[PDB]
Image (cartoon, coloured by chain):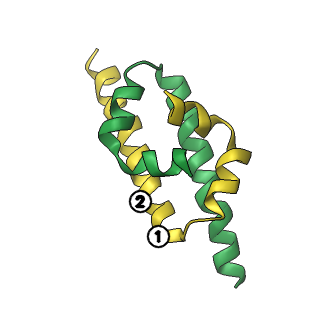
Chain colours: A green, B yellow
Amino acid sequence: SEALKILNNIRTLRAQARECTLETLEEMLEKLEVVVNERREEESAA
Amino acid sequence: SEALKILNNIRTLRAQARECTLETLEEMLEKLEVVVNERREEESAA
């Protein structure tokens, strides 16, 4: 879980976002939303 | 940008999410939303 722990420090991701375009940032937000929604389905099923 | 490129592969984040609780996943989604919104402000200003 090295990529999940980095998401907790926004300042670190802030420096990484400065080297990427907005279109790549939109795709990254989609994947994180699906990952949280995937766990939401397991929480709603239990 | 090692944490930003990992977010593109949801299957990889999928295995990492299985080892964390939903509360930690909610905070991670907040940071990514703020990172994308921070770049949105720069795009709207330009």
Separation (CA) of disc 2 from disc 1: 7 Å
Q: Quadrant of residue A40?
A: bottom right
Kindly indicate whether the residues beneath marks 2 and 1 are on one polypeptide chain.
yes
Residue type at tag 1: Glu
Report the residue marked by disc 2.
B27
Please name the residue that numbered disc 1 is placed on.
B23
Dot 1 alpha-carbon crowd within 10 angstroms: few under 14, some 14 to 19, many 20 or more: few
Question: Mark 2 falls on what kind of element?
Answer: helix
**Dividing the picture into quarters, in which one does residue A15 lie?**
top left
Tag 1's secondary structure? Answer: helix
Q: Which amino acid, by three-letter code, is at mark 2? A: Glu
Circle 2/circle 1 CB separation < 8 Å:
yes
Residue sitting farthest toward the bottom: A46
Output the chain of dot 1: B
The image position of residue B46, as x and y in percent, is 29, 14
**Residue drawn at x 39%, y 51% as measured from the top left:** A8
Residue B29 vertical position relative to residue A28 in the rendered view, above or below: below
Residues packed near mark 2 inside 10 Å, few (<14), some (14 to 19) or many (20 plus):
few
